[PDB]
Image (cartoon, coloured by chain):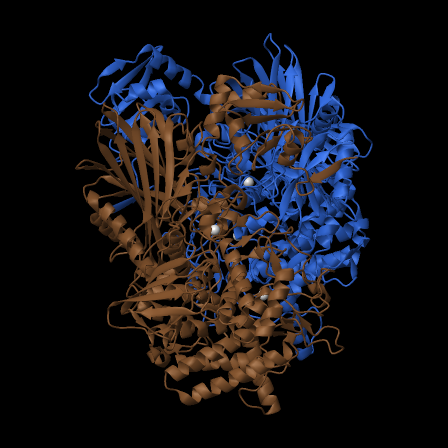
Chain colours: A blue, B brown
Amino acid sequence: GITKVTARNNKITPVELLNQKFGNKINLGNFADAVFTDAAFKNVAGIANLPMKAPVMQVLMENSIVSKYLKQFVPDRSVSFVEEGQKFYIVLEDGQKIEVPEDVNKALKATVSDVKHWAGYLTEDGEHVIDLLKPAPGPHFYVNLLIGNRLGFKRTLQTTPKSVVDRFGRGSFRSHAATQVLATRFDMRQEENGFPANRQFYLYEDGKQIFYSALIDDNIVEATSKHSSNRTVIKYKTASNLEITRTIFLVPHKKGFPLATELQRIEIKNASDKARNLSITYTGMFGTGAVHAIFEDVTYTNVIMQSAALYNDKGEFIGITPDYYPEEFKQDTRFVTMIVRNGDEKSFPQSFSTDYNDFVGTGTLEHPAGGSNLNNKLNRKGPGFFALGAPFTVEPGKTVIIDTFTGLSSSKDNENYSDAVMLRELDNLLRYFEKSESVEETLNEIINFHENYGKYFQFNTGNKLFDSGFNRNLAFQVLYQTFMSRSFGQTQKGYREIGFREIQDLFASMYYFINIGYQDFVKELLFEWTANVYKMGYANHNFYWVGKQPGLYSDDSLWLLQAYYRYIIYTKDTSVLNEEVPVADGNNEKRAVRETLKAIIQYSASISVGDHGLPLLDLADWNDSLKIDSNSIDGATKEKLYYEQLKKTNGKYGDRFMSDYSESVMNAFLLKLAIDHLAEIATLDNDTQLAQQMSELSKEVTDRIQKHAWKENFFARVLINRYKDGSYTYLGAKGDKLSADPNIDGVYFLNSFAWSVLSDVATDEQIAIMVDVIKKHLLTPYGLRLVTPADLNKIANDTATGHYFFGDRENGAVFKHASMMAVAALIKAAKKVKDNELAKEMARIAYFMIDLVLPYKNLENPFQVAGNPRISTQYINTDTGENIGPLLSGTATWLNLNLISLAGIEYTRDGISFNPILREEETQLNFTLKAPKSSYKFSITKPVGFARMESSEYELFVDGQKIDNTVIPMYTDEKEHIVTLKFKL
Amino acid sequence: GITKVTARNNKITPVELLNQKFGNKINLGNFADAVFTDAAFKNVAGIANLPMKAPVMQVLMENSIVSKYLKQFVPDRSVSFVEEGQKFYIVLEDGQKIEVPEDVNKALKATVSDVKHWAGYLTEDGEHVIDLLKPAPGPHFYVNLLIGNRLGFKRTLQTTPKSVVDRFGRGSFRSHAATQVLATRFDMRQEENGFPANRQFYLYEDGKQIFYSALIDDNIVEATSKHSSNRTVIKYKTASNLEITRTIFLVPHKKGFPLATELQRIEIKNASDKARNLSITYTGMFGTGAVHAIFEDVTYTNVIMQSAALYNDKGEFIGITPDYYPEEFKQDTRFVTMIVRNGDEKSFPQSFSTDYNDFVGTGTLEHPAGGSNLNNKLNRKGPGFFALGAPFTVEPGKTVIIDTFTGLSSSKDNENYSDAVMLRELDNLLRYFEKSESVEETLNEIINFHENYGKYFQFNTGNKLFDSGFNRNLAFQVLYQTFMSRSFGQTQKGYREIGFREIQDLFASMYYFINIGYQDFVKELLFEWTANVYKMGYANHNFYWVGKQPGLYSDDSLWLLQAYYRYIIYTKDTSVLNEEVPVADGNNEKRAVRETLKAIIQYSASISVGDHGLPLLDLADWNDSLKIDSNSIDGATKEKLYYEQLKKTNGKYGDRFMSDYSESVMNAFLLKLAIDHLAEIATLDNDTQLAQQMSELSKEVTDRIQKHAWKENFFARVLINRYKDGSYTYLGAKGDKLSADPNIDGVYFLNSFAWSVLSDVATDEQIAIMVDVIKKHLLTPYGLRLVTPADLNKIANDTATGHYFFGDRENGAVFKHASMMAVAALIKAAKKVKDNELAKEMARIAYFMIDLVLPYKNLENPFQVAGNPRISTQYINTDTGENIGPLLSGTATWLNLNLISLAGIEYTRDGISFNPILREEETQLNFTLKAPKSSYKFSITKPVGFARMESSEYELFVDGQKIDNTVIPMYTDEKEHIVTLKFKL
Ligand SMILES: [Cl-]
Ligand SMILES: [Cl-]
Ligand SMILES: [Cl-]
Ligand SMILES: [Cl-]
């Protein structure tokens, strides 16, 4: 009877049908576009010889002339557009070639003239210029992220405002935690992040709507947007010679200011020869305080709040605020205010509206019926919709400025908070910005701050796109992820706390902060993370104001050692070891940092270990899908049981916790790295005995890993101890009998090899074997996948079936974070392996994987790979090659680390270890580095081909003096030092 | 500095300013409209002498001519429009009167011509006719509810489809539980219930959009909607002489049909003299299976599903379905299909689109750029947006029909479910509706079913609006609430289970169902509710497939006795007492219904009692705000502790559970009523000894209530036992020291009096005293409020400080359910009190309260009271008088019961007790009643003034024979009996 055909089961594509029908008749070129003309997929209509893949037929069908002309042929007849000479022809399946009329030819040429830049382009500074009339390659492609600046104030990690702005100005604005200033929309589409009325405005002339900022109509002749670092600029040109500019950014915090403030400046210039009397209506929607009640009870959200008006000391209306009855929703107060600067005179809105139904009327949001006549009625219910209207006359050649301040004041930064505090802070903010030039000065301050922040490491390679992407975009993303973790984004709209392992972000940004005089901020972050470690050694999984989920995951506390090692090595500041930080257990208890690190190592190395001595897997580790044990316990219950066992067995503290739980090998690698880091810290702190115990413990752990985790072709991922019959003993190598692919003998994890190399456990032969294995199995045309297919139901029957189609997330996708860690391991191995061929192959693999994650390269084939040309995405779909969000992940952090490492810079106790690994085709690499008391200018020259310090003669000069030691000293003479490296044939 | 003025603090209204500026100059009439011209509220513009309150100035400002004319006076001057001699003038504050121009006069006369019908009107059948161009009085005013018909199938209460449709066809469509067929929107506004594209379509001619069903533009000359019982009809007329009709309803279930199916028929008639070639694009959005992930992870919702196409046996495309990868989301399969009927020719959609971005393009949803050229591309991701396009030619004077079937198949009605089951069921449904007249036959079947269902009680007064509201609208609402409880609505969008006390709905609908041959359905509902009672006597608070929250609330199980008593009294079917129903404890255990009722009575009367012997309050009772005890326990904990106490103290089953918890007096009234009901059931079942024990227990309970609950003016609400010092001992009468109002001595609860009268506990003197107290304190101009202000923090210092402004919900609002119970108590008292003046006063109060809840009376002042002219709302705002939803509540059930009781019909062991209570101004009341084997025609005549059988001589005739007994026998002779009552002065 009725049959069903799915999207993935439809094998034939329109382009394939077009190639079949017209391949031997016309030259299809390298790229072409096509569309099915009917629901039976029998006939196609397309255009040939495109410069790149693009939805050209979708744009063509929107043209009335072209669609009307095509109606003579389609459906029931396949046609193709072909350009010959300077004219366009239509070709049918019978070989007939017909010259199109003049209007059709003109429309076709105008459409296909600029296909190469349909998705935009990047300037020399890495800013993305977007045409507002073009289709979006993906939901994250045209997204910009804005952040505040709470440096030097309390609770910087928890109180920094955040915002997401798209190409049209749409998006949302959030204060501390998940508090909303502008409304966030939770709907079916990924493109709808906020309420559609946010940040939009209307322009009226003579009572007729002449402009809407979120709708490009026939009266707009030019409309472009520019995404830059922490600011967005949108430009419009109208047919009546009006030039409109919108600049959106976030105000850096000053004393007496509200906690969150977003500034939008609208400049309207009259390029005509006649004065024009216009009016502006700026609209928006406040975010509700009862987010759960949106899904629970919308009427509750509506009836608990009302609208209120704000007046200055002269009694003039200035803006609207939402007023809440319940006390819990009175701890934050929102506001929106408008100032109209006409030449030297200042004015304030003359009308307002607070009801969506009255404002829209019988029209739509794009053409509201009551937009030009605001009723000045204060709504007694929610939601907090607002529309402020003001008239103004602009003279020929003159400009009128409109400054809108949206924001929120909170009790999180004030004592005895009330609405009076909000009024005082709003008065301070308005007095600060009473002059026109103050907004420009603040914008310049933001730009200069980010430019100076990015100065720690500067690339100079001639490739402007790469230099801009690293020096500006990547540095900003690292700062943003340091301040925000993974809590906000275009599609990250729920409430999320800061994860412990997200300390990984501080692995990259700290060197930047220390280089702008904010070493104390890095110390504060380190102590804040240390405060979430319990006395035994486990840590809270998440924390925003307080910690939660104690010891839920077994790998969390082991990441802190890497951050402490990085900070102490870079700064040589061991005094942080003596700092007394509160313990996560509580009850006014404090411990020295050194003792906390010792407790972490002891917990992961002696107490929470399995039969083979490797750390217990517990519920899971870094890999969230490794739910091998269904009877796992957290830190608190494990501690209680451990104390019970100690009292029963009459043992001593530090003994093994008896159990039959599984062991994590990646946890063992992390523990070994942490032990080595603590040994280095102790020997830097003149703690000889502690260094000795750390060294012997590291040797013992390495012996255990080599004895019990190496399975003759790979390092295992999990060791299983609960099957006494021997049915299953390990997972993550050959012979584990858990592979779900008949053609693959065993399961293989990328992280196993990555952290075997990173922890300096694997040997050269093991490195070569694992590299061969990952080349055979884990390498895909779109990168390196996290893991080969596995059948975990045999050992854990409680695991459910899959949730994703092939190529998505857990079903064979390429996760860029894990791939970046693997690339770091490959670089580290290639820097020191004896075999030159193995090093060359590993460097080639690393560069191949790096080329797939650089955001700017997303603009080469934007409509196939999607992603974002300035911000890193999460993973790559192995079925289509498309980059899919969210935009916040460890990809940016580990990519920055990998690029710096490939430049050859490493930090050790003796100073700067230099060991660059350049591309085979590269012949020159120049960059500049900053140190707290010096600067370095590195230049490297080499011939075409692979070259490295390990197996190639070279000349190294520091300050013009030839040197043999590759460790550059960390100078403190406040002088610039020139370093030159030359590779010979 | 900056000051803030809230909506409630702005005392001066525009109408007050208009009255103070023009009151002594022109005649403003009884009603007027006004609007502030500026944000300083200094000047006003308005229109005088309106027939009723309406937003006339909002509509006037939308007129370009009127707005342009007004722009020459406002905002600097205050103006008023006045009609004098069919000519409009404008009046200024200086006394100047100016005749408006001709166009302004024409627009003004056209606008205010039909102000009285701006919110619509009701037909003789109670159907609401709505103009699509007029403002909505409230978010629930233009809402219609549609329900399916699963009678005679399995799990009717859990599998009946439901739908909400507004005046434009917007809304949503749901299946079993909260399963969505069409997408539900969770946003800030109450008006947005579903996705905007649901049930909407576009009409194109020559590639240009000529019609959109959700937007009224200048090309539409007529646009009206009609809300009827279980169907919605919308009509449009275009300037090009096109007549469009949409009919939306739900298909009653048949064997082999899908579980949920919504049918929309679109008829397009060409009233011109030329044949027209048009095309239709019907759009919509499927509901997602991962509702929580919408707020959690929108990308997850997008990537777990794809689009698929459906083809018939001939290989022709017929529709779109969403295909899910995860197993848990594969248990339901959605579908949308289209059929085009051109005379006898049948055709299917020729194109489709499944991407929102491609469909909308550079336009909007109202004017999509790719609407006329669907790309026929199956989306690989979500959401399930669909748009089906088909062309057709309509001849002059001819009609083209388009039938769209949306729906869902589920595993809840099938075994070994897969998509093949959905395909087979869809094939069955399409085969059933292959003829054009099948849709009309199904619609007529629905109409006839509801007409026949409403025939149990038929009023035959002269109002013709009250008759329609009761006979059709109220009966349908009672049926809808019986099937749906309080789970769905315009603003009720979350997932809700069936509450136990919602058995109250069956109090009213059962007599209807029994009278259409569905007594077995009522028995099934009774047994389903009985299955949720535990062995001890408590019950689950909620249940959809299984019960949950055992014994959480102390009043739940006591409501079942009333339902059983009603059923047994009406049907005389005591065999239900012998039925073996599973107990809620489980483990294959069954108990007779009689034993379950006995256990309920024993639990509420002997075990779960306090110091005074009244039932324990536990967490709460019917009143959810009575959280007096913060250490309350549920049924399971209480049972475990009771067994521990019994074993410790060597007691026996049936002894009191020792504690110091509070006691609920309303629970005591419910228990007394249940005991009386069980006594009546026992004596009807020839169970003499059980009747004797029930009688003595009822006497003991009455003695306890009279001794311990009556405090010198009122019946207390809660008895407090945890203060040995005597600081607080009771709440809900005079002297409880818990009043929050200094002018009120004590707190007073309406339900206390209501259920004292309803349980036949209060005496005549107590009734008079409580009536006086209610008139003094609990009576407001907008009805009877639930409770006087109270300060519960003195005994329960853990509750919040309040969530609502004055007049909303818990803060002094009039809850219509509690008011209806109080009205029932007033009617019952007035039917039997000795004092004629007291009975007259109580009847007057009851009728005054009833006049405030009748939905049709909402059309008298629609723009002030709002509500819904056909469906009851929840409560009335005591600050403004506005009716606020949701539309589902016990108001409808108790209003139906109250109206039937006021008609004088009661059911007792001897038959029909007759005791009408008519309005003072009424002089004639005729109605018809149905009994399972007979029919009655009641006529009552009386002079002007209060009259009742208690204190007035009368003549009663049955079948022409004068009788003295007022109990009409329940005849079973299948004949109509005439009953006549005459009241004489
Ligand atoms: Cl994101
Ligand atoms: Cl892993
Ligand atoms: Cl509702
Ligand atoms: Cl109550």
Residue A922, x across and y down, in percent:
56, 27
- Is there any visible trace of residue B607 in the rendered image? no
Nearer to me, A846 or B194 = B194
- Residue located at (72% from left, 54% from top): A530
Q: Is residue B296 left or right of residue A971?
A: left
Q: Quadrant of residue B435?
A: top left
**Outermost residue toward the top?**
A273
Residue farthest along the front direction in this orientation: B985
Q: Is B756 positioned to the left or the right of A8 in the image?
A: right
In the depicted structure, whether residue B503 falls above or below residue B324? below
Toward the left, the furthest residue is B344
**Seen from this angle, which residue lies furthest bottom?**
B650
Quadrant where the C terminus of chain B lies?
bottom left
Residue B538, given in percent of the width and then of the height, sits at 50, 75
- Report whether residue A674 is seen: yes
Vertical order, B232 against A341 (above or below):
below
The x, y position of residue A478, in whole percent, is 64, 38
The residue closer to the viewer here, A684 or B4, is B4
- Quarter of the picture containing the N terminus of chain B is top right
Q: Residue at x 59, y 76 (%)?
A: B616
Could you tell me residue A297's position as x and y percent? 54, 52
